[PDB]
Protein backbone atom coordinates (compact mmCIF):
# COMPACT_ATOMS: atom_id res chain seq x y z
CA UNK A 1 0.00 0.00 0.00
CA UNK A 2 1.26 3.64 0.71
CA UNK A 3 2.82 3.03 4.17
CA UNK A 4 2.44 6.21 6.25
CA UNK A 5 1.62 8.75 3.45
CA UNK A 6 -2.19 8.48 3.81
CA UNK A 7 -2.28 9.35 7.55
CA UNK A 8 0.40 12.08 6.94
CA UNK A 9 -1.91 13.76 4.36
CA UNK A 10 -4.95 13.51 6.74
CA UNK A 11 -2.80 14.90 9.62
CA UNK A 12 -1.81 17.85 7.38
CA UNK A 13 -5.48 18.49 6.36
CA UNK A 14 -6.41 18.24 10.06
CA UNK A 15 -3.73 20.74 11.34
CA UNK A 16 -4.79 23.20 8.53
CA UNK A 17 -8.47 23.01 9.65
CA UNK A 18 -7.39 23.82 13.30
CA UNK A 19 -5.40 26.88 12.11
CA UNK A 20 -8.52 28.07 10.15
CA UNK A 21 -11.03 27.28 13.01
CA UNK A 22 -12.37 30.22 15.15
CA UNK A 23 -9.65 31.33 17.60
CA UNK A 24 -7.09 28.82 16.28
CA UNK A 25 -4.58 31.67 15.63
CA UNK A 26 -4.00 31.73 19.45
CA UNK A 27 -2.25 28.28 19.13
CA UNK A 28 -0.40 28.88 15.79
CA UNK A 29 2.97 30.15 17.17
CA UNK A 30 4.86 29.91 20.49
CA UNK A 31 4.69 33.05 22.71
CA UNK A 32 8.21 34.64 22.86
CA UNK A 33 14.41 35.38 34.46
CA UNK A 34 10.98 33.74 33.88
CA UNK A 35 8.61 32.87 36.75
CA UNK A 36 8.90 29.16 37.72
CA UNK A 37 5.09 28.56 37.36
CA UNK A 38 5.12 30.09 33.78
CA UNK A 39 7.78 27.62 32.51
CA UNK A 40 6.15 25.12 30.11
CA UNK A 41 7.40 21.49 30.50
CA UNK A 42 6.63 20.62 26.84
CA UNK A 43 5.84 23.70 24.64
CA UNK A 44 3.87 23.04 21.45
CA UNK A 45 2.16 25.01 18.64
CA UNK A 46 0.48 24.27 15.26
CA UNK A 47 3.63 25.63 13.46
CA UNK A 48 5.83 23.06 15.33
CA UNK A 49 3.43 20.25 14.30
CA UNK A 50 3.39 21.48 10.64
CA UNK A 51 7.24 21.46 10.65
CA UNK A 52 7.38 17.80 11.88
CA UNK A 53 4.89 16.86 9.10
CA UNK A 54 6.95 18.70 6.40
CA UNK A 55 10.22 17.13 7.71
CA UNK A 56 8.71 13.62 8.11
CA UNK A 57 9.51 13.35 11.87
CA UNK A 58 6.36 11.41 12.94
CA UNK A 59 6.76 7.62 12.87
CA UNK A 60 3.18 6.73 13.98
CA UNK A 61 -0.34 8.30 13.65
CA UNK A 62 -0.68 8.54 17.49
CA UNK A 63 2.42 10.81 17.68
CA UNK A 64 0.65 13.57 15.68
CA UNK A 65 -2.45 13.32 17.98
CA UNK A 66 -0.36 13.46 21.23
CA UNK A 67 1.34 16.72 20.03
CA UNK A 68 -2.07 18.28 19.16
CA UNK A 69 -3.58 17.14 22.51
CA UNK A 70 -0.45 18.62 24.26
CA UNK A 71 -1.46 22.13 22.97
CA UNK A 72 -4.94 21.75 24.56
CA UNK A 73 -3.57 20.22 27.81
CA UNK A 74 -1.16 23.21 28.15
CA UNK A 75 -4.06 25.57 27.34
CA UNK A 76 -6.25 24.23 30.21
CA UNK A 77 -3.21 24.13 32.57
CA UNK A 78 -1.92 27.73 32.10
CA UNK A 79 -5.40 29.36 31.73
CA UNK A 80 -8.36 29.60 34.19
CA UNK A 81 -11.33 27.39 33.13
CA UNK A 82 -13.60 30.50 32.89
CA UNK A 83 -11.16 32.51 30.64
CA UNK A 84 -11.63 33.30 26.91
CA UNK A 85 -8.46 31.32 25.97
CA UNK A 86 -9.51 28.21 28.00
CA UNK A 87 -13.03 28.26 26.43
CA UNK A 88 -11.50 28.67 22.92
CA UNK A 89 -9.13 25.77 23.68
CA UNK A 90 -11.95 23.40 24.74
CA UNK A 91 -13.90 24.30 21.55
CA UNK A 92 -10.98 23.55 19.14
CA UNK A 93 -10.23 20.36 21.16
CA UNK A 94 -13.85 19.16 20.57
CA UNK A 95 -13.48 20.16 16.86
CA UNK A 96 -10.20 18.19 16.58
CA UNK A 97 -11.61 15.05 18.34
CA UNK A 98 -14.76 15.10 16.17
CA UNK A 99 -12.62 15.60 13.00
CA UNK A 100 -10.67 12.39 13.97
CA UNK A 101 -14.04 10.53 13.71
CA UNK A 102 -15.28 12.27 10.50
CA UNK A 103 -11.91 12.03 8.61
CA UNK A 104 -11.48 8.40 9.80
CA UNK A 105 -8.11 9.21 11.43
CA UNK A 106 -8.96 7.01 14.47
CA UNK A 107 -8.91 3.93 12.15
CA UNK A 108 -5.12 4.54 11.62
CA UNK A 109 -4.55 4.73 15.41
CA UNK A 110 -6.57 1.48 15.84
CA UNK A 111 -4.50 -0.20 13.05
CA UNK A 112 -1.30 1.18 14.72
CA UNK A 113 -2.08 -0.28 18.20
CA UNK A 114 -3.22 -3.64 16.71
CA UNK A 115 0.18 -4.09 14.95
CA UNK A 116 2.33 -2.78 17.87
CA UNK A 117 0.71 -5.06 20.54
CA UNK A 118 0.84 -8.04 18.08
CA UNK A 119 4.62 -7.66 17.40
CA UNK A 120 5.46 -7.76 21.18
CA UNK A 121 3.34 -10.92 21.83
CA UNK A 122 4.31 -12.52 18.45
Image (cartoon, rainbow, N blue to C red):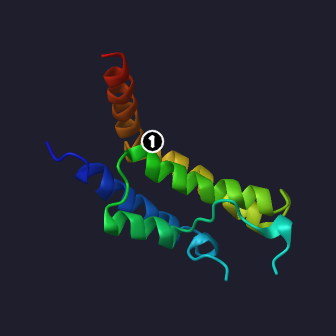
Q: At x 61% / y 76%, what residue is drawn? A: 30
Q: Is residue 72 left or right of residue 84?
A: left
Residue 71 position by quadrant: bottom right
At which x and y percent is residue 103? 38, 47
At which x and y percent is residue 83? 83, 65
Q: At x 16% / y 47%, what residue is drawn? A: 2
108 over 86 or under it: above or below:
above
Q: For the view shown, which residue lies furthest in the bottom direction? A: 32
Can residue 99 be seen here? The reply is no
Q: For the view shown, which residue lies furthest in the front direction? A: 33
Residue 13 or residue 55, whichever sits in front = 55
- Bin the neighbour count of mark 1 within 10 Å (Cα to Cα): few under 14, some 14-19, many 20 and up: few
At which x and y percent is residue 107? 36, 36
Q: Is residue 21 left or right of residue 112?
A: right
> What residue is shown with label 1?
101
- In which quadrant of the rendered image does the C terminus lie? top left
State how many labels appear. 1
Q: Is residue 68 left or right of residue 82?
A: left
Q: At x 35% / y 39%, what residue is drawn? A: 108
- In which quadrant of the rendered image does the N terminus lie? top left
Residue 64 or residue 18, whichever sits in front = 64
Q: For the view shown, which residue lies furthest in the left direction? A: 1
At which x and y percent is residue 90? 69, 55
Q: At x 85% / y 73%, what residue is drawn? A: 35
Q: Secondary structure at mark 1?
A: helix
Can residue 49 be seen here? The reply is yes
Amino acid sequence: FQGNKQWYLLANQLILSLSKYEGGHIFEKLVDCPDYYDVIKNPMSFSCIKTKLKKGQYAYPSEFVKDVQLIFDNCSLYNTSNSVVAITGKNIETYFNNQLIVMGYNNFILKEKKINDMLKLV
